[PDB]
Amino acid sequence: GQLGEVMKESARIAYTFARAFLMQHAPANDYLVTSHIHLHVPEGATPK
Amino acid sequence: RMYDVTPPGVVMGLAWTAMGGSTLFVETSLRRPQDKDAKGDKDGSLEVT
């Protein structure tokens, strides 16, 4: 979805926090760390 | 002086700008989860900006 690279670091950060929150909440699930995922953010937001 | 506690990885730096001089800060941060592979051996490439 027309990522600017800054949006890419933000995305990776949010990803890692998701991965941590699951094991903090429901350890038995492992959906995030064991599967590929496409994610789409529609363009339009200004970079700042 | 924008930051006061200076959270890790930010440092002051003087700069002799085109008019006068100003105390611009320098900043850095991670860009990917670090332990992508505990055995991984790939250079931790920098990205200047």
Image (cartoon, coloured by chain):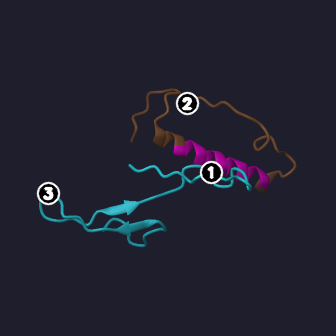
Chain B display color: cyan
**Distance of label 3 from label 2 (alpha carbons):** 40 Å
**Of discs 2 and 1, which sits in the foreground?**
1
Sequence order check, earlier mark of 1 and 3: 3
Chain bearing tag 1 is: B
Let me know if residue A1 is in the magenta part: no
Q: Residues within 10 Å of mark 3 (few under 14, many from 20)?
A: few
**Residue under pointer 1:** B42
Residue A28 position within the rendered picture, expressed as x and y whole percent measured from the top left: 87, 49
Residue A23 position within the rendered picture, expressed as x and y whole percent measured from the top left: 78, 53
Instruction: Count how many numbered circles sit on residues in the image.
Output: 3
Give me the chain that's brown.
Answer: A
**Of discs 1 and 3, which sits in the foreground?**
1
**Residue under pointer 2:** A41
Q: Residue at x 13, y 64 (%)?
A: B20
Residue B39 position within the rendered picture, expressed as x and y whole percent measured from the top left: 74, 55
Same chain, marks 3 and 2? no
Q: Residue at x 37, y 62 (%)?
A: B26
**Distance of label 2 from label 1 (alpha carbons):** 29 Å
**Residue under pointer 3:** B18
Let me know if residue A12 is in the magenta part: yes
